[PDB]
Image (spheres, coloured by chain):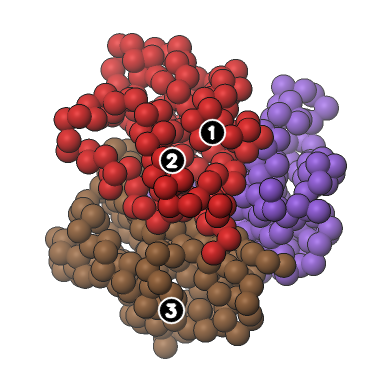
Chain colours: A red, B brown, C purple
Amino acid sequence: NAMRIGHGFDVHKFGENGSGPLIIGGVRIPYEKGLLAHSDGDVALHAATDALLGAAALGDIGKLFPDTDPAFKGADSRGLLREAYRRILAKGYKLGNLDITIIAQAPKMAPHIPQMRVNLAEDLQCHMDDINVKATTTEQLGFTGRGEGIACEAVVLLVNV
Amino acid sequence: NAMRIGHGFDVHKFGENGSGPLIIGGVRIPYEKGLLAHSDGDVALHAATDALLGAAALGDIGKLFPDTDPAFKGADSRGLLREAYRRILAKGYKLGNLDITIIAQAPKMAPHIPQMRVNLAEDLQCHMDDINVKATTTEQLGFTGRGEGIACEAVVLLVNV
Amino acid sequence: NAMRIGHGFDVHKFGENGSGPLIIGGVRIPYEKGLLAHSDGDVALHAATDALLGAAALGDIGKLFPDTDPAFKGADSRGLLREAYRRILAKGYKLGNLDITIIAQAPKMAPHIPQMRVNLAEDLQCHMDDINVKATTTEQLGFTGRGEGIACEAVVLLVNV
């Protein structure tokens, strides 16, 4: 039972032309709209969490932190990540590595990726070499391209201890 | 050559407002429309199969079970899964673990996941701990959100014997 | 640090009704439009590259080959792949296996997959058994289904040397 694979996927619709400014990978990114979600609305962490729990066959964030429950209204996605990893460790697994892809027309994710990596390496208690983050656009096609929300895909490897 | 990775992806358009009621992960889920496909139309099994065959570098379900061939009109996706695994075993591989994500606005996948896991653990001849299933919506965005079909992504790890 | 996982994702919008004819997985496929990209516009290689670099926590193709830089206007995606792998080897990793899924309504990818596999096995310097390629459509749904562009997802396993 040496190694386990996991996959995550999250999308959030953009809000009004208010503020937010969208938080992603625990980083506050200036933008003229934020994302609409029951929680912090951080698609990168949501997708990373789902990957982790999925690898551990623990379901997903829903299965750990009921979406219905008012205790998680606006809750910090970094907190959820951190709890999820505590459970994974409990079960005798440890992060191998993590690869994330943000899918967004705008804003540019590039400048914020180093800090995102810092946050995750901190949260999954590991060296920053086990964390990789990418962005791409869909060349203006589909709802991400039409500019309506952003999406995120994650892929994870867990190692036995 | 210790371990091999695989990825799958399937989508089916919804039919009329007839019946179906859609079958997914081998589970019959009540819903006012079913999916339109040449076979059973089970996106979770289709995507899981593709992942498995992909990891084994065996192509995909097309390469094993010609879509053109009338012998697979309405064929049980569980049967196809089962044959595909027989071939994978033949080649000296065995499931490590499987993680699936269903992408759908409605109906709720939650209540049916335990049974889906039972079906796969049965079919891939393994303990149910090596099988993980998740759902998410795309927050009403895109064709899954517009309610037009459902999509499924799968990720697999094969181990050498 | 035995094995590392990676994920890639690319999409390109179709051009006019001119020529192109679209190049994918290094194969020239007859079609009445080609893809619109700053480079060769080969979504299969782009996604494969991103997976590789992602597994190596090296960022993505952007981080190696600035999109802004005029030296990569129309550049061969096979060249980029090849350079990326040189860097991965430099860091003590080697391909385990690769699985790719092309997502397209038309044209049919089927007949070209053997040759695509030849190109990659050549480029990643390995036996063709470590390379798997698939296509699917989205049953005419979404922008791939509406026929507006094609998309590609890749998944990779790197082994330590």
Asked if residue B36 is positioned above or below residue A48 in the image, the reply reads below
Callout 2, which amino acid?
Answer: Tyr
Q: Give the number of the disc on residue B111.
A: none
At x 69%, y 48%, the residue is: C1
Callout 3, which amino acid?
Answer: Gln
Q: Position of residue A131 (x, y in %)?
A: 60, 35
At x 66%, y 35%, the residue is: A129
State which quadrant residue C115 falls in: bottom right
Res. B11 visible in picture? no
Callout 1, which amino acid?
Answer: Gln
Q: Which of marks 2 and 1 is nearer the N terminus?
A: 2
Given residues B22 and A157, the one toward you in this image is A157
| Residue most extreme to the bottom | B71
Distance from disc 2 to disc 1, alpha carbons, whole Å, reads 9 Å
* Same subunit: marks 2 and 3: no
Tell me the subunit letter for badge 3.
B
At x 49%, y 30%, the residue is: A123
Residue under pointer 3: B125
Q: What element carries label 3?
A: loop
Report crowding for label 2: few under 14, some 14 to 19, many 20 or more residues within 10 A (C-alpha): many
* Same subunit: marks 3 and 1: no
Residue under pointer 2: A85
Q: Are marks 2 and 1 in contact (CB under 8 Å)?
A: yes
Q: Is mark 1 on a helix, strand or loop?
A: loop
* Same subunit: marks 2 and 1: yes
Distance from disc 3 to disc 1, alpha carbons, whole Å, reads 35 Å
At x 21%, y 70%, the residue is: B28
Given residues C95 and A97, the one toward you in this image is A97
Residue under pointer 1: A125
Q: What element carries label 2?
A: helix
Given residues B156 and C32, the one toward you in this image is B156
Q: Position of residue C59 (x, y in %)?
A: 67, 33
